[PDB]
Amino acid sequence: VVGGEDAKPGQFPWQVVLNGKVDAFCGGSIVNEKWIVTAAHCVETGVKITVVAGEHNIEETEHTEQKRNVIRIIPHHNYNAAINKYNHDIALLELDEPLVLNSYVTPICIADKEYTNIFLKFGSGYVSGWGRVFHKGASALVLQYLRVPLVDRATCLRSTKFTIYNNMFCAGFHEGGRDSCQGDSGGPHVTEVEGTSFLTGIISWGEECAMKGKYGIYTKVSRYVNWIKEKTKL
Amino acid sequence: DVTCNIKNGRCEQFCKNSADNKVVCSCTEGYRLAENQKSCEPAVPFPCGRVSVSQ
Ligand SMILES: Cc1ccc(O)c2c3c(nn12)CC[C@@](C)(NC(=O)c1ccc(-n2cnnc2)cc1)C3
Ligand SMILES: [Cl-]
Ligand code: NA
Image (cartoon, each protein chain N blue to C red):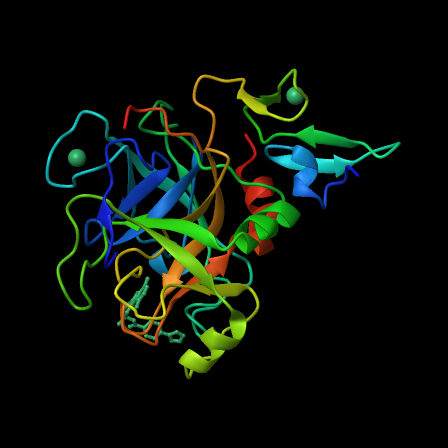
């Protein structure tokens, strides 16, 4: 996250960080004690992943972290990286042993398809992650967060050479300076509804973090709610 | 006039249109619709989407 602020402990208790060959390479969100939602481009069947919930500063033990092994990876059935690494860019991770829910490890709410879309239409969400804090710069140690406004479809289409399909949205600022970045992929875009946060997007990609005239591109979660609910039901 | 299209029926989370110019509010998993018929109160120890650690 470029242009963000340090989260306080427990401020985004649904955030997770993923570790694999490289530690802290993508984000995710807690759906329930056994399931994480992330981006499909972050994961692949066969490559071993661990999830860390309750994380804040990746370089200090804070006595709230819970590490779990991923036993199943479910990319969305329409995901196909050979066609487009970033379309239908969503996946579910099943944990080996359930998380212990507490004030530092709390699921994100997921509304039905209609309301997830209404909430995205409110036009302002929060993104968070341990990704780069400058384009091609260092990654964060302390979880970063940022409020990003929804960018209207016409503006985002005029800003990129790539086609942005209707199952994606754009968010960010006309002047740049504030954006998600590499390493934040798979993390949450959430909308606060009277003090309760709902998942409205998955952080997916962008061309140049925080560059004026470019925006962050997000997966619309409304398009996948039924699939998430079906697959993660306990 | 009371409908889900107007201020979400004054429902804190979700609204459904019902009979006689009324609405029925509801909440996500882990919350209960409160006695005021609009608000959402926790019904489990760690409901989703809530910050509980002192900020
Ligand atoms: C999550 C995010 C948010 C905002 C960002 O600017 C951002 C970046 C990257 N991730 N990222 C990867 C590296 C970075 C240089 N981007 C990329 O390397 C990049 C390049 C092309 C695509 N793409 C191809 N077809 N559709 C999309 C996607 C990503 C910048
Ligand atoms: Cl109820
Ligand atoms: Na830590």
